Length: 205
Ligand SMILES: NC(=O)c1ccc[n+]([C@@H]2O[C@H](COP(=O)([O-])OP(=O)(O)OC[C@H]3O[C@@H](n4cnc5c(N)ncnc54)[C@H](OP(=O)(O)O)[C@@H]3O)[C@@H](O)[C@H]2O)c1
Ligand SMILES: O=C(O)c1c(Cl)c(Cl)c(Cl)c(Cl)c1-c1c2cc(Br)c(=O)c(Br)c-2oc2c(Br)c([O-])c(Br)cc12
Image (cartoon, rainbow, N blue to C red; front, side, top):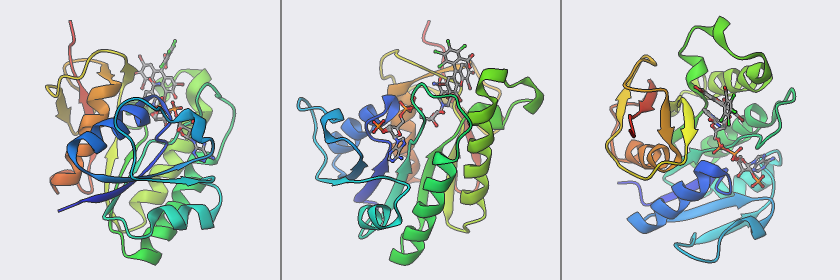
């Protein structure tokens, strides 16, 4: 079973709760962070912290070495500009996984990669184009890859009661950040989603 994981994007909205949940669940967690002040003092703490950048192959290599699986929650925070950060990061992650024998990656893009592709809001098209590039990198890697394609990420509580479909239709167009992290972790203990795209959603009201 998976025991050691690396999380990329651990200081982001979804990353922080995925990190806390992973530690609480008993995983030995390594994170790559550019700025360690963005990790919390309170609550569960990662076992290992690598300071560095996902665009630097050597930093990624140090983070992936010795792991059983990788969770990818990279993103651009509020920046909607044209970008290759996520896809170039994914290229480095795949290379490091292959160099170190790691064969399982669970990575977040977005439900826009399941929905009608002519229906992406213009302001999100540039980020979506890089999610598509990252999905291609991961699909073509040959590694066991679970593509997680969430709708709007909300602040609702953790429930563990969301629905996962394979086609982008479901009970709602929202998933709480906590539930999304819980799902990422679920993907570490089953092979049922390997090679598939997944759509987690739930009605919180
Ligand atoms: N917002 C939504 O409703 C929504 C819906 C569906 C999908 N998505 C997608 O879901 C994914 C996760 O979203 P989120 O809101 O949880 O993410 P987020 O808050 O934007 O966090 C991005 C994370 O990636 C890290 N990162 C960015 N560039 C990096 C670099 N060069 N090296 C190392 N780490 C780097 C950030 O580090 P720092 O802390 O150092 O900045 C942060 O940890 C994103 O790809 C997003 O586009 C979002
Ligand atoms: O209308 C939006 O898209 C939007 C707006 Cl208009 C506002 Cl105000 C806010 Cl806060 C957010 Cl989070 C979003 C949003 C999002 C909303 C819905 Br509905 C949805 O189904 C999906 Br998929 C969404 O994907 C996003 C991705 Br990809 C991002 O990287 C960011 Br950044 C924001 C979104």
